[PDB]
Image (tube, rainbow, N blue to C red):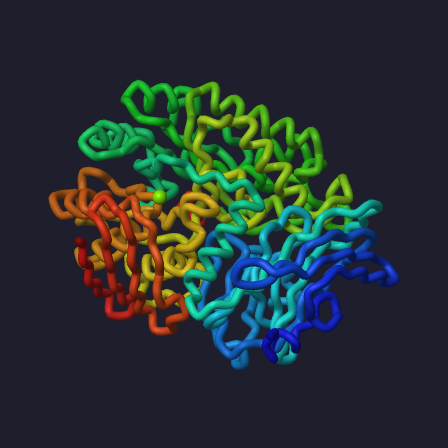
Length: 533
Ligand SMILES: OC[C@@]12C[C@@H]1[C@H](O)[C@H](O)[C@@H](O)[C@H]2O
Ligand SMILES: [Mg+2]
């Protein structure tokens, strides 16, 4: 039998049932199939014309839903769908909140997937359209947004799955396995360890301080030595240094001379209003009414988005990342990637998602198969198959964040929450990056118990482990936490109670380097209890 709830769903406006169907509307045509798969149903097919904001599924909204923001920093969390209040959106960061901000300013929005107890609805890809859900007058509606682009000939729909089982974590894991297959996900066999400058030195990093850490890093179990934001003269001018830094090429040569894999931060789809590249090439950016469209404001400057539909832009990206590879960099943290997918006017009439994918594909080609790509500030689904690792929460911080709301400002407590709630993408989409461990004992307000809680959770989850500290300031305790963390890697994790609303989670991982383990963590009390077999 079906189920009363399944007879009550609509697929492309028709009553739900298994079959093969054609919708011919005024401005578009859809051909689609509704087919049985393990644990549920798959809706797939093809579309042509001007589909616009295309309705795919409609069903009664659940009371409590696990919602997901489209990008690295945005929350994945359980919300009450009936008492939802639209947020005030910061005009300087509009597009990190939503790629369709008209939705978010009036209704609850979830990107790519949404879950309730016993049921996952999820799209398998975002190659052309942006897939998202909205709660509109008590109804859950799935959409594919094509951003007013027209298609003369058929292109594939992003597939939708509807999965049901009482084990919600199992469904999220299955969903993510299907996403990995649809997109030829990269799941490296080896996970890098390393050092990152950001969460000690921030923009005030000097090359003198960098060299001091490079010598000390020889006593710590680090493979990668990554320079973050600070070295560059302006956003977009990635090969021009400032302050006491040598050349970008010389930085690589010192780092490699000292026995590390050189790593470097860029924001490659972003160019500031002051940069040489923007002032040389005003034509290279996404536009609004013919003029440069602000993508976001950061570093106290307007930042514009590179128009990734333009071959001149893609050639510049190729040559940049080719040059970096020639210098010896083999670890690339590529940040603020949402900029490349902002809605706006481009040279070619392609979607922002199509443009985005051309840009990241160009970066991968340039750095080669032997380079590690870490995505950050990024749309998640469009990057599967391209990146090796991906930041999946908001920034951590050398403090827990007692007065920081769940709003995107840095805080260890909210960074950790996302590592938990997105755990199922790990070893399926890519390697999850939970953000850096901060293990120093001076110049921090983190307690030893908070450092433990953060680090051991990241280990049980088998996530990337990168440390970000002035290494002078890390002593016995910080060293022991890093050692014991690395002992918890290598397993298959599950968060058992993924729909929890009180920030206490039970987490198991099978087959770690320490055997079967279990950690119960409480992000309100700041406590954990870890058992290892
Ligand atoms: O600017 C470097 C910086 C702060 C911005 C971003 O929030 C990223 O997620 C951080 O790890 C840093 O690389
Ligand atoms: Mg693994």
